Amino acid sequence: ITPGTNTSNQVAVLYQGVNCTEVNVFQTR
Amino acid sequence: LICAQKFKGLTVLPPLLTDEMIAQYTSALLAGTITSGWTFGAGPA
Ligand SMILES: *[C@@H]1O[C@H](CO)[C@@H](O)[C@H](O)[C@H]1NC(C)=O
């Protein structure tokens, strides 16, 4: 997830389907 | 079974609008239909 290279270079990763306990963080469905 | 087919590369993505948001939209539409009628669809309620 990125706001666009024209405005920023920060990105966020989303691992679709894991519980994120085998790899800020916010646990989602 | 979802956790018998997910082990073959298949993944079920959750919808954007959850059941609670759809229920809130339905309740808002019902309240607008009961109180205002057809005025809340064209302009103000
Ligand atoms: C997922 O993480 C939650 C919160 O830490 C934990 O309660 C739960 O046991 C975890 N489930 C799995 C499948 O790892």
Image (cartoon, helix red, strand yellow):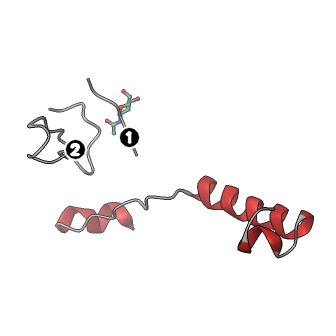
Is tag 2's residue or tag 1's residue first in the polypeptide sequence? Answer: 2
Residue at 72 percent of width and 74 percent of height: B42
Give the residue furthest to the right. B35
Q: Nearer the viewer, residue B37 or B9?
A: B37
Q: Which residue bears the numbered disc 2?
A: A14
Tag 2's secondary structure?
loop
Disc 2 and disc 1 on one polypeptide chain: yes
**For residue A10, side relative to residue B17 (left or right):** left
Q: Chain of mark 2?
A: A
- Relative to B20, residue B37 above or below: below
Which x, y percent locates residue B16?
43, 58
Identify which residue is drawn at 8% across, 37% down: A9
Question: What crowding class fits label 2: few (fewer than 14 Cα within 10 Å), some (14-19), or many (20 or more)?
Answer: few
Check if mark 2's residue and mark 1's residue have beta carbons within 8 Å.
Answer: yes
Describe the element under mark 1 as helix, strand or loop: loop
Give the residue pinned by disc 1.
A28
Q: Position of residue A5 (x, y in %)?
A: 8, 46
* Amino acid carrying mark 1 in the image: Thr
Q: Is residue A8 left or right of residue A27?
A: left
Extreme-top residue of the structure: A24
In percent of width and height, residue A3 lies at 20, 45
Q: Amino acid at mark 2?
A: Leu
Picture quadrant of residue A8: top left
Q: Nearer the viewer, residue A12 or A17?
A: A12
Q: Measuring 17% from the left and 66% from the top, which residue is drawn there?
A: B9
* Residue under the image location 35 percent in, 34 percent down: A27
Above or below, B26 against B18 in this view is below
Image coordinates for residue B43, horizontal then vertical, percent = 73, 68
Q: From mark 2 to mark 1, how far is it between C-alphas?
A: 10 Å
Q: Quadrant of ligand 1?
A: top left
Crowd band around label 1 with a 10 angstrom C-alpha radius: few (<14), some (14–19), many (20+): few
